[PDB]
Length: 68
Image 1 (cartoon, rainbow, N blue to C red):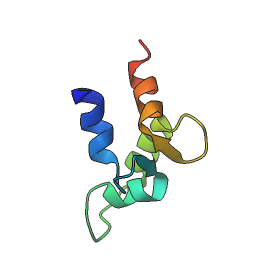
Image 2: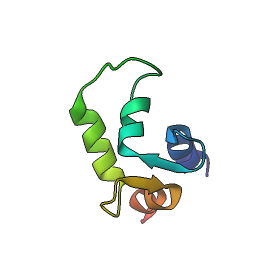
Image 3: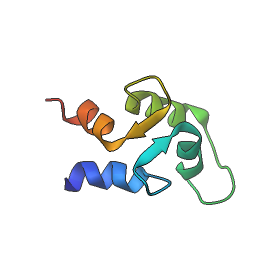
Image 4: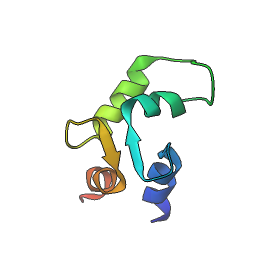
């Protein structure tokens, strides 16, 4: 819970428990202006979405890391 909550619960942009692709682009570096490389943000959200919809709740993230 310290490991998985550390990474996903810090990443959760809205504070309700879900992350989307465009809000991942928002939280990527900043709070305001854009300072980017698309490859980092695109690779990270492709690795984290299990369903192909473009949204993530904590249960998805923890299954793709913790399965073993």
